[PDB]
Length: 130
Image (cartoon, rainbow, N blue to C red):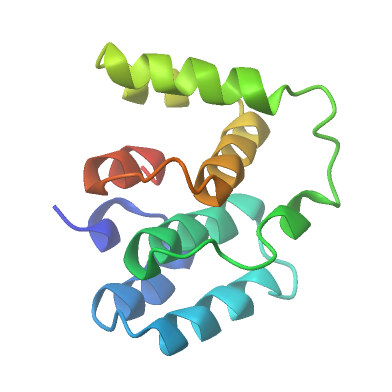
C-alpha cells in the first residue's frame, strides 16, 4: 500500500505531499505547520508526525510539545512501549493499537517517533495511522 490510502482525511494532503517529495526541508515545513496548527485534533498531527518520521528519518522537532495541553499522567510510556513491542513479536500489533484509547495511542506514537532506538518500517507506520 501507501500512507495516503489509509490515513485520516485531515492528514491526507500533508501526507501525500511528503510521500511525493521526501525533501527534508519541505517535509519539515509540513511537520512544523501541522505541529503548530490552529485548532487541529491530536490524532491528525500524530499521523503527519509518524509519516514525517518515516520519510525524513529524523525525530520530529517539538513532538513532545503537542502533549502539553493534555494529562498523560495516567499513562506509563515505558509500559506502553513494552506492550507495543511485545505485540509486534506476536503479530498482534494491529489488535493492540486498536484496543488502546485515543490518547494512549497518540502518546505511544510520540514516544516511538522520538525513540532513536526504534525505527518503524512501513507496515508498522501503516498499522499506526490506520
